[PDB]
Amino acid sequence: GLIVDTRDVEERVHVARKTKLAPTVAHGVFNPEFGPAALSNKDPRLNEGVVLDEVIFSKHKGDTKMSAEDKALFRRCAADYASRLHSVLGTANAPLSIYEAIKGVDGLDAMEPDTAPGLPWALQGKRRGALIDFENGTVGPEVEAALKLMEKREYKFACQTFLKDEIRPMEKVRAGKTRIVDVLPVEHILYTRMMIGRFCAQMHSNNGPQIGSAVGCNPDVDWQRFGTHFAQYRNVWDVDYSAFDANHCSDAMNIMFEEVFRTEFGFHPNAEWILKTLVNTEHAYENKRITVEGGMPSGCSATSIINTILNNIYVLYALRRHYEGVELDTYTMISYGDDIVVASDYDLDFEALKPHFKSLGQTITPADKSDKGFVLGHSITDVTFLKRHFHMDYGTGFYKPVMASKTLEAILSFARRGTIQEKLISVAGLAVHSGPDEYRRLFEPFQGLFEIPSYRSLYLRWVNAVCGDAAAALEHHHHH
């Protein structure tokens, strides 16, 4: 996104914000090249000269202005993908009530009761609970009034930019590449969910390569479904972007919103509008006041779905700008935000698409850091997706998500205070697929201090999850 105006205006003082992540007993064992990001200009781990306030927003390096020809091509692609999408999902995309928007529905989780409220409530000392009743599912007069401004399309707002307290690679920690979460006003999130929550629920339910989205997937069970699909194709690619979200040009964001969220597809007319408000945004960090044109806020409602949709359209766009007679059945893909796996029986030249993605302001390289990359003949067992590989389980003959051992190690190496027991169980579910030997090693440091699940227990849980029939079938016989 293009930073078009900065201001130092106002601000009182910044409260000493530290990281809640503390090392665990595993840190001393694995000695990972990972650390809690910097949350302070005076973090002693930073490199000299690095101003944290500036590096945050360094990702906003412009709003690629697409040519006329390229906009008309982008629209055709956006329409063609919207055609596939709404053919599968249907056209029951009417607004949620205020109740359903808060409480959720099948395929859409409830709004967070006590997360950040946004601006200007954080200044006024009001939590989300003061503005919205989450149990009953009603709204106080402030929200109710704000909503009715959006109906008139006169509503305006600022994004509250927080630093993301999380584990990062140490090179990025030292560089002061702390990620940010743009916290929009609770009423904006609410109304966004009203306008497109029905559609989102329906995309979660329908996750798969047909709609080209993995948002709302359960990697445990769904990896088999995804695995068997992509194994069929001669060629598979996995693609890295640099700052996918930020480099969504306003032209691409605008066209996508117009093509995907049309009233003729069952949406309220203010679906297009509320989404278009994400294009030109104002951001509030401590003292600075940065207005930005282009890019997705990231952390706004439906960020994953929106990014996923754009990713789908970009593939169609890029291919159609290079090759002739390209359609949705020329290839197949699944995406989750910037994350992407494409496959085709055609020998597509993904290296030559580099400039075609650059016309959208996006910069692509292979995840398989080949420095001499994008090659034919890669398969699903070679690629990474949601930080998971696709490996065949010998026992079942089903694909399973295998995370890299260094990543498991880093995730185990740090935790928020007094949540380690809970985090261990959660990560045990991730690490089970790495095999009994590596499982035992990863949890070796924790043995005796905390409850570690048995490899056996989690294996059996997984087999029932992926295929209940299979698990039942193993009991047709009697043992020794």
Image (cartoon, rainbow, N blue to C red):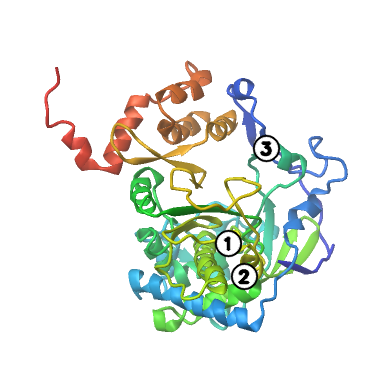
Label at residue 36:
3
Chain-order first, disc 3 or disc 2: 3
Label at residue 278:
2
- Up-down: is 258 above or below 296? below
Residue under the image location 40 percent in, 63 percent down: 203
SS for dot 3: strand
SS for dot 1: loop
Marks 3 and 2 sit apart, C-alpha to C-alpha, by 29 Å
Q: Amino acid at mark 2?
A: Leu
Residue under the image location 29 percent in, 31 percent down: 395
Chain-order first, disc 2 or disc 1: 2
Residue 221 placement: quadrant: top left
Label at residue 300:
1
SS for dot 2: loop
Callout 2–callout 1 Cβ contact below 8 Å: yes
* 469 lies left or right of 290: left
Q: Amino acid at mark 1?
A: Cys
Chain-order first, disc 3 or disc 1: 3
* 28 lies left or right of 95: right
Marks 3 and 1 sit apart, C-alpha to C-alpha, by 23 Å
